[PDB]
Image (tube, rainbow, N blue to C red):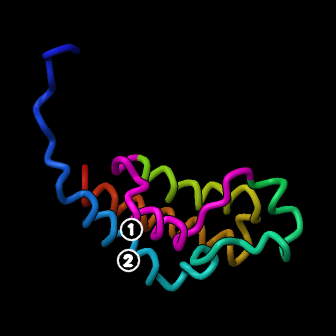
């Protein structure tokens, strides 16, 4: 509360570490469904159904331009990528499986880096 603060967690390396995680996600072989925004002209249903599209390129641009105020808003956008994928794709499809694999990969790196 006012003039009463928890001890300062060092957040000075957060930007660099989120960039590293994002690099690892970008270079994973199963990243291909997520590298670029879904083409809303060419994919029926996507625009109406997925209220907040997100992809790795868009996360990378947001990261590089100071549009994440803290590491939790970064993790929210990454998880959005996988939540969208599950909304639109059957679990038993290549893209559906890609999304489960990538979410697992991400959550481990996240825990190991920060928790």
Q: In which quarter of the image is residue 105?
A: bottom left
**92 left or right of 97 in image:** right
Indicate whether residue 87 is drawn in magenta.
no
Residue 78, image x and y in percent? 50, 59
Q: Quadrant of residue 17?
A: bottom left
Q: Is residue 98 above or below residue 83?
A: below
Q: How crowded is mark 1: few (under 14 residues within 10 Å), some or many (20 or more)?
A: few
- SS label for mark 2: helix
Please name the residue that numbered disc 1 is placed on. 64
Residue 85, image x and y in percent? 67, 62
**32 left or right of 112 in image:** right
Q: Which residue is drawn at 73% across and 55% down?
A: 87
- SS label for mark 1: helix
Residue 98, image x and y in percent? 60, 74
Q: Is residue 114 above or below residue 65?
A: above
Q: Residue at x 38, y 77 (%)?
A: 23
Q: Which residues are drawn in magenta?
A: 51-72
**20 left or right of 107 in image:** left
Mark positioned earlier in the residue sequence (1 or 2): 2
Task: Identify the residue at the far front of this view.
Answer: 65
Q: Residue at x 67, y 59 (%)?
A: 53
Task: Identify the residue at the far left of this view.
Answer: 7
Q: Which circle marks residue 27 in the picture?
A: none
Task: Identify the residue at the far top of this view.
Answer: 2
Residue 52, image x and y in percent? 67, 53
Quadrant location of the N terminus in the rendered image: top left
Q: Which residue is drawn at 76% across and 74% down?
A: 39
Spatial CA span between label 1 and label 2 = 16 Å
**16 left or right of 54 in image:** left
Please name the residue that numbered disc 2 is placed on. 24
The residue nearer to you, when weighing 71 against 64, is: 64
């Amino acid at each position: 509360s006012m003039s009463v603060k928890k001890p300062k967690r060092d957040d000075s390396k957060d930007l660099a570490l989120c960039s590293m995680i994002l690099t690892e996600m970008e270079t994973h072989e199963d990243a291909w469904p997520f590298l670029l925004p879904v083409n809303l002209k060419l994919v029926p249903g996507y625009k109406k159904v997925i209220k907040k599209p997100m992809d790795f390129s868009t996360i990378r641009e947001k990261l590089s331009s100071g549009q994440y105020p803290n590491l939790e808003t970064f993790a929210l956008d990454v998880r959005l990528v996988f939540d969208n994928c599950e909304t639109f794709n059957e679990d038993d499809s290549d893209i559906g499986r890609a999304g489960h694999n990538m979410r697992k990969y991400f959550e481990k790196k996240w825990t190991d880096t920060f928790k």
